[PDB]
Structures are given as C-alpha cells and as structure tokens.
Length: 178
Length: 199
Ligand SMILES: *[C@@H]1O[C@H](CO)[C@@H](O)[C@H](O)[C@H]1NC(C)=O
Ligand SMILES: *[C@@H]1O[C@H](CO)[C@@H](O)[C@H](O)[C@H]1NC(C)=O
Image (cartoon, rainbow over all chains, first blue to last red; front, side, top):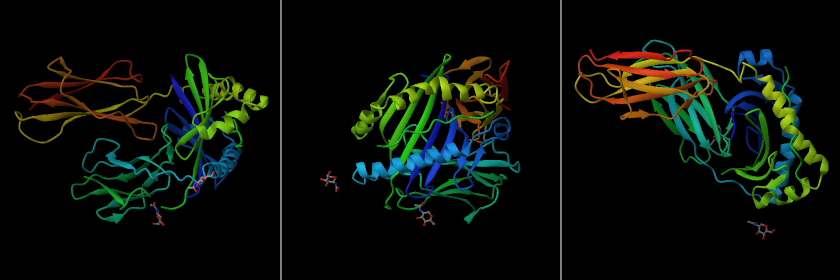
C-alpha cells in the first residue's frame, strides 16, 4: 500500500545481457548504469540535469549479484527456468493522421528469460534508423517486458512489423500494423 | 543532487541461470517501507521487510539465508536503517521533477469507421501523452452521460514517462447528435471537453 513506489532493480544472467542495473519510479525507469561504458544514463534530459548518480553502486551490486547467482546455480542443483514466451502489441504514440510524423511503439511483454531479438520491418525490409528501445524492464511478477520505438510517417501504401525472437518461441513472431 | 544505493547482502534451449535483486521503497502518508527481494530465475526465495524487521525465507530455498543473515546483528541494523536513510533521501530528491510531475493530455474524438449516420459505430476518444496515469474519461450524449456501451482498453504506459488511453462508446448516431468526451486529470485546473457533431 503506497502513494509512490521507488525501486532499484538489477539482474544478472548467463546469456546477454549478462547484467543490468536500474532505478524506476512508479514502474517508469528513471536511470540505469551502462555496465560496459561504466556511465550513468538518465531516461530524461531534466533528470541528469538536476540529479547525479555514482556508477560504482551499479557495478558493485552487479558483482554481489554475480556471486549470488553462482551460489544458487549450485543450491538449486542447476535449475533452469521454463521459457515464458512474450506477448507482443504494436500501437502508435499519437493518433494517426496520414502524412503527419508519429512514433510506432512495440510492447514486448510477459517473458522470461530477458534474452530477446527485436527488429522493426517496413514493407518486408529491416529498418535500422529512427529506431529507439528500452531496457529489459523487470516486472513485479519476476518476468520481463521491453519497449521498441520507430519514428514513422503514416501512409496508406505502408505496413509495419515487430519481429521478435525468444527461446520459448518455435518460430519468430511477427506482429503486423496498418 | 545525488541518489543513494544500499548494497545487496551476500549469499551464503541454451543453458541459462538468472539472479534478480530488488530494493523497493514504499512511500505512503509520510512513511517509508523497505523491501529487499532476492529472486533466483522467477522464484523470490528470501526477503527483508521493514514491517517485519528481519529476513524471511519466501520459499524453502531462502531458508539458509534467513537463518544466517538474521544471526548477524550488523546486517539486520543496516537493513532496518534503510527507510529513514536511502528511501527517505531519494523521495526527498524527487521534488516537482518526479513526485509532482504533471503533463497535460492530448484529446482526439473520431469515429471508428467511415459510413452513414444510421448504422452501428464506435466513437473513439483517444487521450494521449499524460503523467500521472490517474485519469477519468466520461461520455456524454446531448448533455446526458452515457454509462453503458463504453469499451475501454486498459490504461496504456508508453514507456517514455507519458500514458495513453482509448475510450470508445457504442453508438447509433442520428443527424444532429452531440457526443462529448470529458477528461479529468491532476494536470488540469478545469476539465477538457471535445465535441463530435453527427453531420
Ligand atoms: C539433485 O541433487 C540430489 C542430491 O542432493 C540428487 O539426488 C538429484 O538426483 C539431483 N537432481 C538431478 C536432476 O541430478
Ligand atoms: C538472437 O539472434 C542471434 C543472431 O540472429 C542468434 O544467434 C540468437 O540465437 C538469437 N536468439 C534468440 C532466440 O533471440
């Protein structure tokens, strides 16, 4: 029971991403520690402008968590969790108006492990530019979700696809859009 | 200007194992409740709760950790300190930046399908880009509120600190009917209305 929920959520796993550390306020990720660049990344411009964070806290918790994983792989007689396939949804950011630039959001949800491949597709071909994406967001149910974004200009002779790959998926899921 | 972090305690298809650590602060009526969650794969096995005061094996896999951690006076006092320490400081950091962050909604009223003014149709009220997510959307026909026939899709989180919702009413419109969408949000002093004429 709370007015607001402020939380640090960090994971460590065998496959890539091998580790992740972040801070979320009311289910929205505020900041994270890039473990490779060893730098704090803020979700919004105003965040990093008013606030500071020590990346050593991020990494140190990843070190503690790495140890904890080793101890539990042992304790659990090498227990590997069952692959939870994702639930994909594609929807625009703003109401669609032909010729008016918009953003296409791809919500990959309710999966485990956070090992995934996500490619945007326009008219059958891979789109690499005007592309953004979230971290492997840790759901309260110990499952994972992710957001993918594509800046697009709505046209009638166009179709969109969010192509997802997960271990609990027999064939790569294509989730189509107008 | 700087955020604080407590450090987790120490334990004691392709091959893959995961460990998850969670440091949650539950802010309610000037009070902070702290929860330190230790999860192997999807199973939370051991947890510290400021309301409990000590570590508790969530499942039998956390039994050794509950037993050991609770034996160390230092670990226990360190954890107990967290609500008034890290939980409070970080809450205090978020002033009107996160605690009082307000973004006004963009309301668009449009019919679902293009056709004549007699058949069955859905009147979509697309309320987009707002924060916080707490929002009220009411439907009005000729000044009288329509309670029944409202097909809403669960509040949508865009994952960019903005939210969206689509509230559509089932309608059989007659020529000269005025359909009104009424939005109540914390980022508005007065509610925003958008009208739709039959035509
Ligand atoms: C789990 O460990 C026990 C010994 O503690 C052993 O009897 C059991 O066979 C192990 N499980 C597997 C699948 O090897
Ligand atoms: C992700 O993509 C790489 C290259 O396409 C591949 O080696 C890997 O197995 C993929 N796995 C999944 C299921 O995401």
